[PDB]
Structure formats: structure tokens, C-alpha cells
Length: 76
Image (cartoon, rainbow, N blue to C red; front, side, top):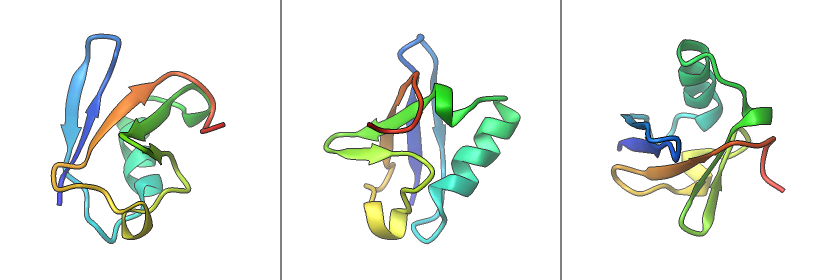
């Protein structure tokens, strides 16, 4: 399994995550290294929202699991 994050700011980065790994840990990890906040950033893929409370084991993401990056505070 692999996850991809396409930043609309012109920044395209892909992060390989596990299908059993919580996006929270990945998002938090990438957010930590990428010094980013969820309350200021939101992730969504197709018809599935990508956030912290969105586990792959549930949100069921695609192989490269490509997610779209969007500035904001969680889904809503």
C-alpha cells in the first residue's frame, strides 16, 4: 500500500503508508516533519475524506492511495 498527497500549492509529494496504519500517525508524522497542522490542512481522495480520524483499514484507500491536500480545519 502507498499513499500520495498532491498539494494544490504546487507541491506534489507521495508518502507510502500501511493499509493497517492510521492516517493520523502518517498525517501526524508527515505533519511533524512537514511542520503542518490538520486544523489548517485537510486531505480528501475522490469521494473519501482524508484526515486524522480516517484509517486506511476503514477509509480503504487505493494502492498508491492518492489523496488531495487542502488548507482548512478537518473535514466539514
